[PDB]
Length: 184
Length: 4
Image 1 (tube, rainbow over the protein chains, first blue to last red):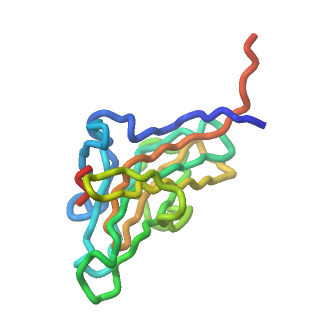
Image 2: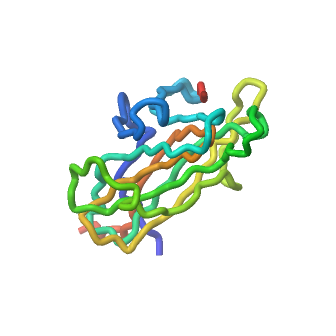
Image 3: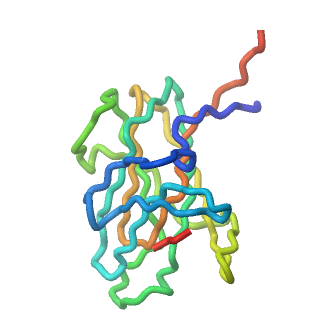
């Protein structure tokens, strides 16, 4: 029952601009290059509009082939700032974000409706996290995985929706499972 | 906001 992983996207091993598409273009999701604890650059996406009303900030990947996989796995590493560490008494601060996908045969889609995106889940910090010493503090780099299928189009677009969190997406790894090959 |  051991399956190999076929990696479709590994954002953390992209060097230079990820070039994902943010809606709005400014004042929502921003690409931010940071150094990890080993001084290795990571392209992150961040937003923290917690002094505003509830948000609707979208970020999407370009098209990802599914290579005729029935099911795809999406692993997100992320860090967030706790709402109880931020000002305001409007009750709008969240510690979650929303994950979506849009299956398409078209590898050059633009200006897509919100209602073409299918919600995968609300993503929250849970038990799975790496502890990273950031000076005197222990940062939780949270790891969450979800899967989708049965897939039926040539590929898909992933999207991330911020509704009012202080959130940084650090890694997006997308893969499917494949039986090991026979070594002729 | 996250500086690495």
